[PDB]
Amino acid sequence: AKRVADAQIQRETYDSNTKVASSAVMNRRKIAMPKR
Amino acid sequence: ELPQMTQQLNSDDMQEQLSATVKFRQILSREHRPPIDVVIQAGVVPRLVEFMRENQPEMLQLEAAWALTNIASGTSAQTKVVVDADAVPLFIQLLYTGSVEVKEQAIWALGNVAGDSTDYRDYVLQCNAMEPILGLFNSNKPSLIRTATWTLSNLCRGKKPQPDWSVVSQALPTLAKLIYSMDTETLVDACWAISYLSDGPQEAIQAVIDVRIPKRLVELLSHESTLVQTPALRAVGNIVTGNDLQTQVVINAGVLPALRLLLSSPKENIKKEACWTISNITAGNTEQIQAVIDANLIPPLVKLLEVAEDKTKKEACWAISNASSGGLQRPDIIRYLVSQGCIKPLCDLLEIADNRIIEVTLDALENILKMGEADKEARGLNINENADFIEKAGGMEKIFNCQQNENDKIYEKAYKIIETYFG
């Protein structure tokens, strides 16, 4: 639940100033419709 | 004039050995394009290393060490030459013996050496440098404490791998005092060293807590200089990756109001770190989520979720979503989030291109829906009020589109949301 930082920031370097689904897996999947 | 100097340095006469070492040190000090390469390639480093031994004048030891230090404070490869000449143990043993001018040179040298990589850092420690270095923080000479602190922090720096904890942790007592210094540079570097030490396992965090550091760090979050804020904020944030008890010490020290201040820093990255830090407190127990709310942190967090830079928004979304966890056992929390207008920004974030965050965002929206549903079932209404807020903010459409996301878990939670609350 806790998250460590992406990287350890440091004095020298610190400066302060994706895929959709296939088609394979889209007719083989159950897409619930709203009502709207 | 140089092949000559190489020979004047090799003379067995002590009088000329000095004169030469002094000329080397001087050219090595030119501000513009120091001749570190040329002096190294004339072969004279191992000769200068000899001039730093116990069996040598106080004035010659100084000049050889100052010349070498100018070398060791150049490029990674010019530092390497000095290390390969076995200069470190004699730098270290000069911290005991030498006068104060000398101590300041060697400590700087060892700082530059320790800062080159995690290898050279470990190596300085293996040579038992920690012990003498701590011995310097008696000196009451501002510039030497300043330098010793700079070096000390470089001995603590680096996570992969960590330095040897049983050695660097002996510096906590000294640092704990140093974060009370009135010298800005000292204070800054002491804070860095703490940020590194606190970045680690629960044993390390507890060490930091047991010397009483966290009270002072919290005080330093409101320092005028962002140079102090940044590493201080970081140390505090690392402490709160710890357990509920550890987190509670920082809250008890007054961190939530300091965090308020930082959520309006002019620097974007201070705001990002403050969001992160708060998010690990809303990740904590139910009292601590309420403390966050009572410190009026939600409203700026929400405002950052709508308008901040992307990296900052993600951190704010974590802070807000983690807080909705505790809505299943305290529904006032969810009600207040909703009422502070967090639905439209959470919705609008679903189209960010980060599957980590989309997931968190949908968990926040599900928790809002779950409490909006148990609100209408508990008092016999025919509408989920939150479901309609999400709908009117174009978030149903956005959640719907998440079924077309490659990650199965995203599709699955999204599918579940449209069925359960939009059927």
Image: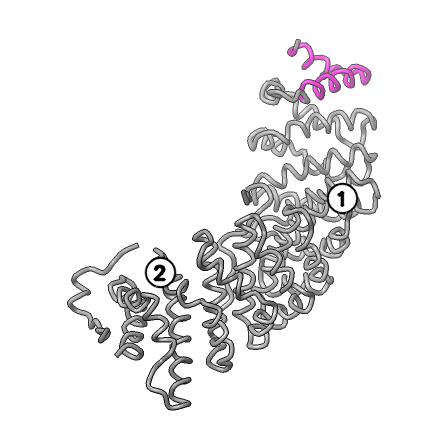
- Tell me which amino acid carries mark 2: Asn
**Could you classify mark 2 by the number of other residues whose Cα lies within 10 Å: few (under 14), some (14-19), or many (20 or more)?**
some
Sequence-wise, which precedes: disc 1 or disc 2? 1
What subunit carries mark 2? B
Looking at the image, residue B48 lies above or below residue B231: above
Residue under numbered circle 2: B355
Q: Residue at x 34, y 82 (%)?
A: B383
Q: Is residue B111 left or right of residue B174?
A: left
Q: Label 1 amino acid?
A: Asp
Label 1–label 2 contact, CB within 8 A:
no
Residue B334 on the magenta span: no
**Residue B230, image x, y percentages:** 61, 50
Residue under label 1: B183
Q: Which residues are magenta?
A: B2-28
User: Is residue B184 placed above or below B334 in the rendered structure?
Assistant: above
Q: Position of residue B296 (x, y in %)?
A: 58, 67
Q: Residues within 10 Å of mark 1 (few under 14, many from 20)?
A: some
Is B409 located above or below residue B91 in the figure?
below
Q: Secondary structure at mark 2?
A: helix
Q: Chain of mark 1?
A: B
Q: Which residue is pictured at 64% across the width and 27% down the height? A: B71
Q: Nearer the viewer, residue B24 or B175?
A: B175
* Residue B181 placement (x, y as % from top left): 77, 49
Count of labels in the image? 2
Depth check, front residue: B81 or B155: B155
Q: Quadrant of residue B141?
A: top right
Q: Position of residue B1 (x, y in %)?
A: 66, 9
In the displayed structure, does residue B384 sit left or right of residue B298?
A: left
